[PDB]
Length: 307
Length: 303
Ligand SMILES: CC(C)=CCC/C(C)=C/CC[C@H](C)CCOP(=O)(O)OP(=O)(O)O
Ligand SMILES: CC(C)=CCC/C(C)=C/CC[C@H](C)CCOP(=O)(O)OP(=O)(O)O
Ligand SMILES: [Mg+2]
Ligand SMILES: [Mg+2]
Ligand SMILES: [Mg+2]
Ligand SMILES: [Mg+2]
Ligand SMILES: [Mg+2]
Ligand SMILES: [Mg+2]
Image 1 (cartoon, chains in turn yellow, brown):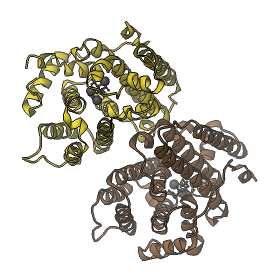
Image 2 (tube, chains in turn green, red; image 1 turned 30 degrees about the horizontal axis):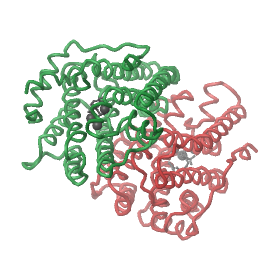
Image 3 (cartoon, protein in one colour; image 1 turned 60 degrees about the vertical axis):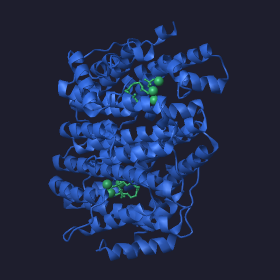
Image 4 (tube, rainbow over the protein chains, first blue to last red; image 1 turned 90 degrees about the horizontal axis):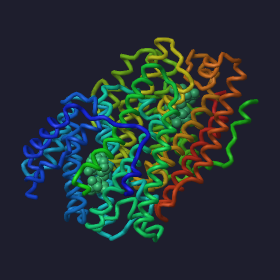
């Protein structure tokens, strides 16, 4: 049982609003027409129960935006990774031109699809809770996620599996984890000054947490990705580069995950002293990264998505 | 004296267009009424060293941009607006409008018009993703300058950790690093452009350029009573002599040079085309490190 090795020297938490938020996410999906034919299965999506773990101290209104955003990501992701649009760059470019217009604050038009309308709704709701500087940073992380998904599409279309270095570098954006990390600021109601927000050690803590979450997901989701012939997965990329067995590739992936956990724990104590207020806010942010690491693992072990 | 210790284990270069670009930067600065000894500014001779392989058209934008920063910088560091937050917020609101695409209005100042001209010219050479990354770095430069202004007004000195973190943005070096992509005509994929090792190389090069400037510019900054300088921040934190503060700043500079050349050997292998483009970008960081030092030692600005 290789899944037993996905362990951390810290624990997570869940918002008491978890089930209320999950039911509201299903109602939001229905409202914006994101629930496709494939009804009874929708009851066990449980996207709100991941959000509830990722932002456990958030007010219900803010948690609901995070939950709806996570739902959006899964709906978009399953299109990219399991349907035709993921093998069609020109279709994806056309869609992303609409998303990018909506991220700049353009109102959707009659011809726009459900996902564009739903994105516009999330941007509108975030604009009410967040200042302009935050909105710009979130939008750029979402833009980089679109860029990364266009890159994954070209790989699928050309039948090309990236090397480990390229995959790991791209994975940091293809999973939209940085955009989710931006929501921690709103969940914790913290205003980090520019010099603290972008500090090298904070960036390295963000990178480590992102790698941990993505590589944990890669170990839990290689089976379903193999079924669809999509090798955007640390296990499958390691297998191709090292020409090794699947058990060996899984073992190597878990070793990289364990090393990245140790790196995160180590760098947590390398945060320099700015002032009392800034460091208090900074420790709430870094605590947020730990909640996310645990949320991903705790939710993913209990989800039929990876069964 | 202590200036002799500002050394690098690599060399720079200068564009053959250096003098016509510098002369054209003066002409541009006069045209926009940014001039009010002009021939001794030599802002084009910094640009020519920073982007030595750039085509003349692209180098001219870079030179005009560097001139813009110096004009803006002297107003912040030697003039009243640098000790007036609400006035700076008003000016920055006009700049941020221009950066988003808004055309200047009747009673916008010379700088706002000059910034709009630079944005227009950059839009002809660079795609939207580039313009956004550049705009964000310039926005963080404005934010860093507003932070410096609050410090000046309250007569506050930040600790070394706070100053170094803020200095990375107050110098606009990242905005200048963005221009390397255009100078060198390279298109780095997202995953290489934002790679942790590339970020750490940019941070090291930024630290080196800023701390080199701090050692060469502490005299003129003391005269204006400005403490945004590694030497002066070290002196305040450690309560040491000025010679000891300079020695400590130069040790941090030397240590950062060692870090930069070490992390150059830690760049992963992505593919042939990407690593070819990356090595041109990282070489660009080296050109900038050398350009800053080479230009500053011959500039009357720090005499
Ligand atoms: C769906 C999405 C992009 C984000 C949802 C929120 C989130 C940050 C989840 C953590 C897991 C991981 C980063 C998803 C990566 O996509 P991948 O396609 O490998 O996910 P899958 O294995 O579940 O399909
Ligand atoms: C003027 C400016 C923002 C940039 C021009 C181009 C550039 C990146 C020059 C390198 C020197 C340094 C980063 C300037 C920092 O401002 P500081 O105020 O310490 O400069 P000074 O010492 O020359 O006054
Ligand atoms: Mg997927
Ligand atoms: Mg995916
Ligand atoms: Mg997966
Ligand atoms: Mg200055
Ligand atoms: Mg300055
Ligand atoms: Mg200076």
